[PDB]
Length: 312
Ligand SMILES: [Ca+2]
Ligand SMILES: [Ca+2]
Image (cartoon, rainbow, N blue to C red; front, side, top):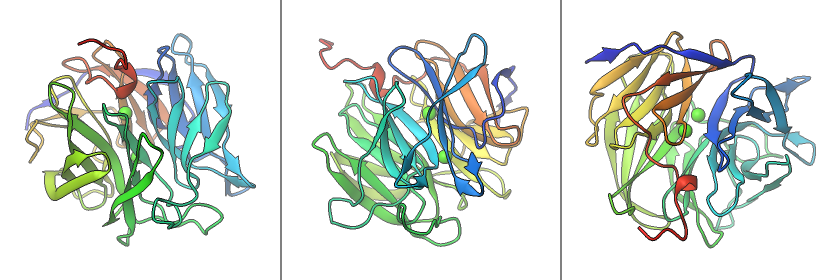
């Protein structure tokens, strides 16, 4: 498999469990620090990074009734410049730029208690597909599906429904949505970390997925596997292979990677493209840092980059 070795340039450092990189509607950059702790208890943070200086500013330190969150993944909204954040303890959060936030769901559409989330992906229809590898949200005792298959998948719809669309995953992690050229959402890709698998589903409509399939295979037998993921403008899927020192590049049809990207570290965690560029910001756990490198092309536009009142 072809492997490229692009220059990785340092962005920022010392962010415990550096995760969920995201750009907002203003082009501002954000990173989540799920692993920040205060006396052994979770006290996760959501930070804004000044790309010019690399200086950090924590805008939000989410906690509900004394229970600190473990913010792990982000997506920027389109109709409002707010961030939807997958939290391993609090579920789904909506965080404002001023640092204020709200807890979206205690329970799903079936009245079942909400599970802690890790990552999420907005489709062009505005529906948010979320991976839920943790057990029930706080106040429940923290649990994660690294060993047992109780990880779930949710779809938070435009009409405000938190619908569990699937479950029985062994740590569902990264997630991405494939769209047709006309903008129609038609395939969901879900990373199941320890099993070294990328699963796919046909999106038949909002909160409606069918035909679960093993879409791709993540290289290596190291501890870890597929973490964060995103598509480039040609629909190639770049997946951070935690523990392999590489970001895998799958073609539109999946299977085995068609190329790998060597990182100057062992634990790439998540990645995100800078709008209108080929620049991919990469978070990694070895140094709890953020880097950036130039990919072959621009990234696929995130939902936040689309236009509600767009003519074409
Ligand atoms: Ca993740
Ligand atoms: Ca991303």
